[PDB]
Image (tube, coloured by chain):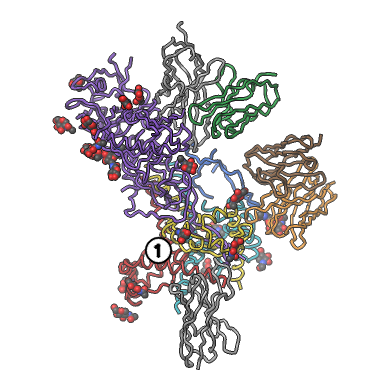
Chain colours: A blue, B purple, C yellow, D cyan, E red, F brown, G green, H orange
Amino acid sequence: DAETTLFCASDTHACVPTDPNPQEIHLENVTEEFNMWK
Amino acid sequence: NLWVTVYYGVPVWKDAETTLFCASDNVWATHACVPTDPNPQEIHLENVTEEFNMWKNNMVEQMHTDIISLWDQSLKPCVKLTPLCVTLQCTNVTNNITDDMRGELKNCSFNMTTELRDKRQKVHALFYKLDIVPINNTSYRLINCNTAAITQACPKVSFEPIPIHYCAPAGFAILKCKDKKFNGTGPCPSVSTVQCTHGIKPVVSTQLLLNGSLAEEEVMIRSKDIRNNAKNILVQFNTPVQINCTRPNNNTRKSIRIGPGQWFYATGDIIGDIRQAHCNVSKATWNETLGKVVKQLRKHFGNNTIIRFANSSGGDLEVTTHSFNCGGEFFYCDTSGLFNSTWISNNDSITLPCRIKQIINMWQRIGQAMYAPPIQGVIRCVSNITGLILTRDGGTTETFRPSGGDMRDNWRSELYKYKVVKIEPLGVAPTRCKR
Amino acid sequence: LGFLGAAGSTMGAASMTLTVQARNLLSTVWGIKQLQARVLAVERYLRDQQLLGIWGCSGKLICCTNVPWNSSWSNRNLSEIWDNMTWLQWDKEISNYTQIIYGLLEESQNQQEKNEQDLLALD
Amino acid sequence: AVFLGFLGAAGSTMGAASMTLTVQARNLLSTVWGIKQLQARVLAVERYLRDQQLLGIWGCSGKLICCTNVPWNSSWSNRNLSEIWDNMTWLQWDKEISNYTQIIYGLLEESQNQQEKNEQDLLALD
Amino acid sequence: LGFLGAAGSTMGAASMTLTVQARNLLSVWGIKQLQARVLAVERYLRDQQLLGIWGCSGKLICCTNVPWNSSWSNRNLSEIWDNMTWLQWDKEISNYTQIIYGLLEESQNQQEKNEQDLLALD
Amino acid sequence: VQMTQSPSSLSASVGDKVSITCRASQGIADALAWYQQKPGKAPKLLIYGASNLESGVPSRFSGSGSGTDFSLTISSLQAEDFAVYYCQQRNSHPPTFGQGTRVEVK
Amino acid sequence: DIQMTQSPSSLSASVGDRVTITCRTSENVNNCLNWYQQKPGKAPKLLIYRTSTLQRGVPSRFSGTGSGTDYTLTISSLQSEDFGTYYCQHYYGTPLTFGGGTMVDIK
Amino acid sequence: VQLVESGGGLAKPGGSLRLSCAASGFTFSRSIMHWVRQAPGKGLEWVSTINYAGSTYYADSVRGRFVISRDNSKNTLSLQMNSVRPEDRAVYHCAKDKEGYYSGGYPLWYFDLWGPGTPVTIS
Amino acid sequence: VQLVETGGGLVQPGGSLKLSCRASGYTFSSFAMSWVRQAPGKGLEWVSLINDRGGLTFYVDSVKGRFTISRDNSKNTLSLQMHSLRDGDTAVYYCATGGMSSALQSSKYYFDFWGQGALVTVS
Amino acid sequence: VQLQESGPGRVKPSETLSLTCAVSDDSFGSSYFYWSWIRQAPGKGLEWIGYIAYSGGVRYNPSLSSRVTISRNIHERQFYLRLTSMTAADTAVYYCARHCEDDYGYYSAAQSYGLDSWGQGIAVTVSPS
Ligand SMILES: *[C@@H]1O[C@H](CO)[C@@H](O[C@@H]2O[C@H](CO)[C@@H](O[C@@H]3O[C@H](CO)[C@@H](O)[C@H](O[C@H]4O[C@H](CO)[C@@H](O)[C@H](O)[C@@H]4O)[C@@H]3O)[C@H](O)[C@H]2NC(C)=O)[C@H](O)[C@H]1NC(C)=O
Ligand SMILES: *[C@@H]1O[C@H](CO)[C@@H](O[C@@H]2O[C@H](CO)[C@@H](O)[C@H](O)[C@H]2NC(C)=O)[C@H](O)[C@H]1NC(C)=O
Ligand SMILES: *[C@@H]1O[C@H](CO)[C@@H](O)[C@H](O)[C@H]1NC(C)=O
Ligand SMILES: *[C@@H]1O[C@H](CO)[C@@H](O)[C@H](O)[C@H]1NC(C)=O
Ligand SMILES: *[C@@H]1O[C@H](CO)[C@@H](O)[C@H](O)[C@H]1NC(C)=O
Ligand SMILES: *[C@@H]1O[C@H](CO)[C@@H](O)[C@H](O)[C@H]1NC(C)=O
Ligand SMILES: *[C@@H]1O[C@H](CO)[C@@H](O)[C@H](O)[C@H]1NC(C)=O
Ligand SMILES: *[C@@H]1O[C@H](CO)[C@@H](O)[C@H](O)[C@H]1NC(C)=O
Ligand SMILES: *[C@@H]1O[C@H](CO)[C@@H](O)[C@H](O)[C@H]1NC(C)=O
Ligand SMILES: *[C@@H]1O[C@H](CO)[C@@H](O)[C@H](O)[C@H]1NC(C)=O
Ligand SMILES: *[C@@H]1O[C@H](CO)[C@@H](O)[C@H](O)[C@H]1NC(C)=O
Ligand SMILES: *[C@@H]1O[C@H](CO)[C@@H](O)[C@H](O)[C@H]1NC(C)=O
Ligand SMILES: *[C@@H]1O[C@H](CO)[C@@H](O)[C@H](O)[C@H]1NC(C)=O
Ligand SMILES: *[C@@H]1O[C@H](CO)[C@@H](O)[C@H](O)[C@H]1NC(C)=O
Ligand SMILES: *[C@@H]1O[C@H](CO)[C@@H](O)[C@H](O)[C@H]1NC(C)=O
Ligand SMILES: *[C@@H]1O[C@H](CO)[C@@H](O)[C@H](O)[C@H]1NC(C)=O
Ligand SMILES: *[C@@H]1O[C@H](CO)[C@@H](O)[C@H](O)[C@H]1NC(C)=O
Ligand SMILES: *[C@@H]1O[C@H](CO)[C@@H](O)[C@H](O)[C@H]1NC(C)=O
Ligand SMILES: *[C@@H]1O[C@H](CO)[C@@H](O)[C@H](O)[C@H]1NC(C)=O
């Protein structure tokens, strides 16, 4: 787990143009703990 | 039985658009630039033919953007003239004025806040008629006083062009076309690699290209599409035509306080008689230069076509006249004495009257204007006319007129020989070498 | 010949000047642009070094591989590549196949090869 | 695409996931608004170089799989090869060995490459 | 012991702390740190590029095939490794550093790699 | 991602130009393929990548679309093209298929 | 001045019909042709800003092509609103000119 | 280049079935193989896949019940369907993935080659 | 192509000779060179091989510690220095061209030019 | 976007027609745009009168260039047409229009080469009364 500055993709000028790739890689057999409040 | 071999450092590149920086040996902030290389390395590329396109050169748009950004950062900390947008009571100046200058200067008085913010005081200044617009009667207002933010330029920041070298990031290279007959597009069989471009002075002018580089062999006629009369023609001279411009008025300057720590720089008064600003060119040199331009024009439009020069058809003052910055003083010279000739297929000087104005709108933007502070004394500039921006009427005789306005052409006229490429040092090729 | 001087040379002759180009890959207004130029130069240099690492070519300018040349990528003989062609022409010729070759260099060597060396060094 | 397959082996066993080392390697490198982007780009560069420097110090430069001369201590993990390579993933392994990672790195520097290079300096000497 | 602790030590003793110095080369108030970080990275990469083009990538101690020229320094090994520090050596041969680097580039990569390129066939 | 394919009951003559379309519930860039299934037969892959045609498939078939909006165009619907066509996304796991368009002969 | 002959000068069509309109220039305009639809009483609305590139907001039923001096506008399936006068206009130099105009009426 | 399914048939609501699939014209050692099923009222549904390295992926609806396996020496793919339920009625097709850019064995899920399919009925 | 040996031909056992060979009619630096020896009553024997640049030298085991092959590409001269000559070294020595090629050239595993072999007697 | 013609709908013979076109979207101060005046006589097609470029230069129809003056005020976001010596032949609907020539992709969004924005137009009739 880490905290880092994220950048923005879009398709303002503070963001990155050209949109992100929708593609996702499925992590088979990976169980990951999430916490939406943290 | 060949194998893939990886080679790193191959002399391969592709066209690229990247961030270029400044080197130098002020408005253009040349103090922020890296020092230049005292022994520049221009490397000739034998047997390398590259395709160039001066009209699709992304260095021109990058330079234009940088020039505007430098202009604004140099004006941002300077005094705003919002408090000056008051009614002016202007009368005509008559003291030692010749016929050519009658009505050009007005003695305008107004109510300005004094050094304290409570009390007001009456002050006066001289203004050029191009900066003064009637309100409705002797009551006048500054031109575009209520529709734009007029910023006073700092008198301590020079407007003199200083050559700016554009340098490419490591991993990129600038290729230069050494073909003396290159017309701006197509293959260039003689190409060299340069880290950076020669020093390009950010000279801002219209109609005539002042200072800068000269053609190596013959006058060059360069246009995106010579058969399209809506495009500009850039004419590059082999030899310069010298132009001597003056503001023959021993001007004084007054400092009118606007607020704590800041002054409005007013035109004061004029010592001695008042005469009109003007520019001289040699008549014989100009006629010879046009003869050369016509000889080159009669290569595209036919050998038996009459070539005619005429003045600008109209539009903005910055375009109809030859606009330029002479020591920080902005001149608008009437060039109808230069483009007034018919060339048939078969010592003296030319004086161009000039007008002066202090409130200008560079880059043709909405809501922004700059006030050029007065410069005391008498102004004299000697410049090299190195080229022209011409348009053709189009619609047996081809009439050519001066044009301008779009400053990208002035930079394009210098950046026409350069392109930016990116280096791709990692390549693969078959060899008999196996791991 | 200096930087890119061999660009018009044949691939063979140009392959002996690789260090000449390699040395030139690393080295408000005008301040920001300078920093961006420096960061971009570093990122592109490292992207190429990362690929050399993945292929098992780290620290080398000429790296031999275990990936055979496929005649569909180019059917030219060596005398028509190294002796009678420049690297710019070759790059023009090998464009559609660059990602295939890179994927093969990544898979067929320094991945399978390192597992094989891991097993060979076991005994 | 370079992103394709990234971390696909994360839930796979350590052995199977060791066959994808180039997939997770090739995706590691690539106004205040502008400053924030430059910091993110510089950080990606700094982290890449720190890991490559560690590989250099250990004598593993340019390698995805690198064999060493540091014996494995049973105090770090007493699992056998089947338990580690066939019945465990790299995330589980990292959780188990993170307490000993700095010890192992210290040995990789102190117990081998500093001695190996000084000995290689003397074998090429004769 | 520690970063630059061997700076006053002899070249021989100081050669044992190469990782101590090497590991400290990579690691208002906002732009100064970004420039400091970029500068540290560019200097690191220029030195790594030099090691690469000399065939010394990934090494702190790298043996070469460039003979030592007595015109660069005519000292014997005892007076360099046992009776001298690296600061003194650096001062003594700074005038010849670029000559050595040129030779390293020419014989430790350009010639050696083509020879290896040919030995991989025969 | 759910894929909706339409029309489900297309009919045309042996000489007509036809277009079969589908919609993704989420944008999928170009991560889409089209398949052809003859009754009693294995489906055949026609198009991958939305716009790319497979070797062995004639230029008669063409794909288009991006994001959420995709289509398959047949310039001339020959007798061998009357089959159930399927829209399939591979942008996110699990793979999903549309309900299929059954092209009929009038 | 570049002259343009536009044909047909008047066309009657019903809803659902295919409509083709052709412009013939006197000189090559290098694909610098724009097509407009002018309804009576309104300023012409731009349909196509290149020979083939459609203006944003214009239904996909309109298309066009051409080169040299031969350019066409095609309405793939005429709708009840696609009536009025259609014009071709070149921006290849100056003066900018318009064709005579083809009125599309209701059959 | 064909895939031929066998096995299948009828099974009880809590029984088991084995499916087989034989490969003919391709190299059954570098291919990623997938079972996909078509239920009469649902359409094609992906069931499971096994890559060339022996790693398997399952759909959420079948994970924990189905086992996908390959035997390269017989060019055979098989599926052990345990605890089959009424919702498992479908024609089961084996499929081969289009080979693309090296992904470390991660499937693309573009089904380059399909078999006729074998019916499975649960009752 | 013309190849001419200019070396000596009579040495005492234990002595040393140097055989030079001049070449013309081709680019000397583009070809590998070999020395091949033929005893007066025997067939041909390969003795040594030098590449086109001169950095790589190879020898037959029977001479590996005694002979040195070298080439000067500026003077178009090949030479073989033979120390501690044995009675078994009496032979005609041909400064044949070929025997190997660079990785950027076609494989020249043959001797394509021969000429005027020097006769060396050890006695 | 919004181009608004304003001015007299009446000119007497031999007087000058003066029309203003106001631009609402700040594109008047942007590069590669051309601000045109075009007239359409009743029963006729359309006649281009002239334009003023983003650069400040102008171009006129050769048949009208001796009478047409085109000018602009950037700050007020307006351009003007002053057509002298009006006669009966000049009766027409006078429209202002805008087009772009972004030949090399200056803008991040594509601009139209045609007249993608028109005003409503002023019908100008020449008559002594
Ligand atoms: C094209 O090139 C010509 C060739 O030089 C160039 O002409 C030069 O312009 C400069 C800038 O105005 C002139 O220098 C000035 O000369 C006057 C007269 O002595 C001085 O009073 C000026 O000094 C004042 O301004 C300085 C600004 O930095 C202050 O530092 C100083 O304290 C004074 O306040 C200034 O030195 C120069 O004389 C001319 N040279 C000639 C031969 O005419 C021209 O400007 C170029 N044009 C463009 C558009 O680039
Ligand atoms: C996800 O987990 C499954 C279950 O353990 C892994 O597959 C099993 O183990 C090996 C392959 O790893 C095979 O021999 C078994 O037959 C598999 N059984 C089942 C029921 O799947 C699978 O490899 C893992 N997949 C990934 C991508 O990590
Ligand atoms: C302008 O008017 C002011 C009035 O205060 C006067 O003092 C000044 O001399 C005048 N200057 C000129 C040049 O007319
Ligand atoms: C004008 O051009 C001449 C060319 O000989 C050059 O010497 C001179 O310096 C130039 N002057 C200016 C002001 O650019
Ligand atoms: C330059 O000259 C070539 C000659 O073939 C011509 O094709 C090209 O259009 C010209 N380019 C210009 C005038 O920009
Ligand atoms: C221009 O020429 C005229 C000739 O009468 C001369 O009086 C004047 O001083 C000249 N001015 C300049 C600036 O050259
Ligand atoms: C400009 O002035 C210089 C002296 O400063 C003079 O030598 C030259 O002849 C003048 N040129 C023109 C065109 O008036
Ligand atoms: C151009 O010259 C004519 C005289 O021929 C004059 O009436 C017109 O105002 C001039 N225009 C400019 C912009 O100087
Ligand atoms: C143009 O030249 C003519 C002579 O050919 C002259 O009478 C006229 O005054 C000139 N006009 C200008 C504006 O210089
Ligand atoms: C202007 O006039 C003042 C009067 O005091 C004089 O001292 C100065 O030299 C003059 N300057 C010029 C440039 O004529
Ligand atoms: C250019 O070609 C000539 C032969 O046409 C060749 O001699 C020369 O070396 C080549 N230039 C380079 C830089 O290789
Ligand atoms: C290489 O192939 C070309 C093309 O056929 C041929 O002309 C040339 O002779 C070949 N060279 C060699 C060395 O095989
Ligand atoms: C890649 O393929 C295209 C056709 O799809 C072809 O035009 C191009 O030349 C190819 N690239 C090469 C040969 O580098
Ligand atoms: C293993 O580690 C323990 C402490 O965790 C230490 O006491 C022991 O000496 C180590 N043994 C070996 C063989 O490294
Ligand atoms: C490894 O340890 C496990 C205990 O979890 C044991 O079941 C297995 O047999 C052991 N395998 C080997 C090879 O030692
Ligand atoms: C690591 O050490 C911490 C204490 O620092 C301990 O709580 C934890 O259980 C340890 N984990 C492992 C895997 O040894
Ligand atoms: C400092 O010098 C003394 C005297 O030679 C020596 O004993 C000692 O080891 C040196 N220490 C360092 C760190 O160089
Ligand atoms: C050593 O350097 C000198 C000049 O400093 C040079 O003349 C000499 O040839 C060199 N000798 C060797 C063996 O490198
Ligand atoms: C090296 O030279 C020095 C002269 O300063 C001498 O004292 C020393 O003994 C020499 N070392 C050896 C190992 O000969």
On screen, residue B417 above or below G90: below
Q: Where is residue F21 drawn, in percent x and y?
A: 70, 37
Quadrant where the C terminus of chain A sits is top right
User: Is residue F58 shown left or right of residue J55?
Assistant: right
Q: Which of the pair F56/G9 is nearer the observer? A: G9
- In this view, which residue lies farthest toward the bottom? I123
Q: Quadrant of residue J21?
A: top left
User: Is residue F41 shown left or right of residue G81?
Assistant: right
Dot 1 crowding, Cα within 10 Å, few <14, some 14–19, many 20+ = few
Q: Where is residue B323 drawn, in percent x and y?
A: 33, 31
Is there any visible trace of residue B202 in the rendered image?
yes
Residue named by callout 1: E21
Q: Where is residue D66 drawn, in percent x and y?
A: 55, 65
Q: Which of the pair I53/I91 is nearer the observer? A: I91
Q: Quadrant of residue B116?
A: top left
On screen, residue A9 above or below E105: above
**Residue at 46 percent of width and 71 percent of height:** D117
On screen, residue D47 above or below B338: below
Q: Where is residue D13 drawn, in percent x and y?
A: 64, 59
| Mark 1 vs ligand 17: CB below 8 Å | no
Which chain letter matches label 1?
Answer: E
- Element marked by disc 1: helix
Is there any visible trace of residue E37 in the rendered image?
no
- In this view, which residue lies farthest toward the top? J129
Total numbered labels: 1
Q: Amino acid at mark 1?
A: Gln
